[PDB]
Length: 260
Ligand SMILES: NS(=O)(=O)c1ccc(C(=O)N2CCN(C(=O)c3ccccc3)CC2)cc1
Ligand SMILES: [Zn+2]
Image 1 (spheres, helix red, strand yellow):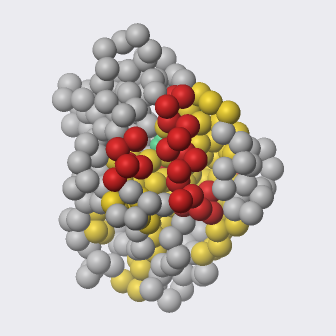
Image 2 (tube, rainbow, N blue to C red):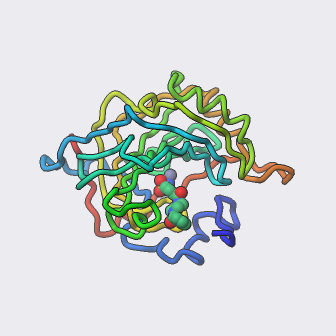
């Protein structure tokens, strides 16, 4: 994507993406509003299994859109299974979407409520061998989405917050070993699920979304550090990395199912 020019500005933001990525107007785009009254309990959903005890983080990268905490996905270490999923999905990275103000930032909404931010733990289906092959399949990825609200600090997030000073600008990375993603989970694994897409270009319709009902709390100081990151590269005019979220897309011919 060396000739990609999409972003979150007025001239290159979500309303423009369809010109280079026509699937932006597709039949299973993400995110969506979760209408809690219309979502139906599905007693057939199997238990959700988040097995992160052997997770091996490697690095954190500012990619000019968000920051990714990257994992070693060359063995079954950190895996997601159960719930709506058939087979085994390996954790490759997590990242966040967040706002300029606490009243916006999430991609999914709940009865039109926007949270301050949203965490995406990205996993790929091991039956397709590599992430690049998985994104070409309708059941290639499983993204576990977790809402953030501003209140108490999340102790398990602080190691991420403190390293951000070293990856301020696009293209900067830092070693980020021994980070435990279990420290970012809420108590309950109750969730909603639906078939959708990547929420950034290339917007591929390859994702089973699993969105947890219980948000995690982070402090105002933690999210303020996210908002000091830059979309720009070093030695370019400063553009704060804020409002890096896609709004809700049409649900079209989809049902959202509840685990609870
Ligand atoms: N917000 S999200 O969780 O839907 C999400 C997850 C992953 C990504 C991502 O990092 N990419 C989009 C898919 N993608 C590819 O299709 C790809 C392109 C080139 C080589 C290999 C893979 C990799 C980059 C973007 C958005
Ligand atoms: Zn995301």
